[PDB]
Image: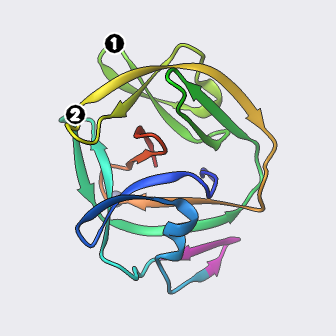
Amino acid sequence: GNAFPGDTRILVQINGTPQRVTLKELYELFNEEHYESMVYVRKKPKVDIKVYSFNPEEGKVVLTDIEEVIKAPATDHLIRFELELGSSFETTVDHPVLVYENGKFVEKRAFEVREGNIIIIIDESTLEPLKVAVKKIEFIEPPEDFVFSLNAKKYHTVIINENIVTHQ
Ligand SMILES: [Zn+2]
């Protein structure tokens, strides 16, 4: 399954306040827990929480509900993307990643992303999108026993680490 490392940060709105939490912390803000089909799923929120998403049909940041958070055993390698200006993120090898090409978001599996592909970051104050190139790609042996994901209602995009737009 597709996932992120637990130390990945995600932009959320908690009780009306925007902030970043790690995916591990996000998982802990839910209860409930059920273990089934080798994964742990939590659906009931402990705080009033929404996730910030990017709506590609309108080019706009939007808020949406979190349907569930998931913790799964780590199996595959991760891929780390280092971006122009020094930001970075990591996903499992087949995780969808959004790159910006010729005026649209292309959804590629992480292992198909190439150096020089463009990633979109958001300026949080103006909500303006900015383009940064992928500068380096690394394959990383899984470094923790569990990885984490979430399902965001409708848009299925999230804003991670240093304001990076990607697919949930
Ligand atoms: Zn849905």
Which residue is denoted by mark 2 in the rendering?
59
> Is the residue under label 1 in contact with that under label 2 (CB below 8 Å)?
no
Q: Is 33 left, or right, of 158 in this rendering?
A: right
Q: Quadrant of ligand 1?
A: bottom left
Residue, x 23% and y 41% (percent of image)?
125
The numbered disc on residue 55 is: none
Q: Secondary structure at mark 2?
A: loop
Distance between the alpha carbons at the discs numbered 2 and 1 = 14 Å
As shown in the figure, which amino acid type bears the numbered disc 1? Asn
Which residue position is annotated with label 1? 102
- For the point 53% across and 59% down, which residue is it? 22
Which is more toward the observer, 152 or 88? Answer: 88
| Residue 68 placement (x, y as % from top left) | 45, 69
The foreground one among 31 and 132 is 132
Prevailing SS of the magenta stretch: strand
Does residue 45 appear to the left or right of 6 in the view shown?
Answer: left
Name the residue rendered at 57%, 33% in the picture.
109
Foreground pick, 77 / 89: 89
- Label 1 residue SS: loop
- Which amino acid type is marked by label 2? Gly
| Span shown in magenta | 35-42
Return the x and y of residue 134 as percentages of the image width and height. 55, 21
97 relative to 160, above or below = above
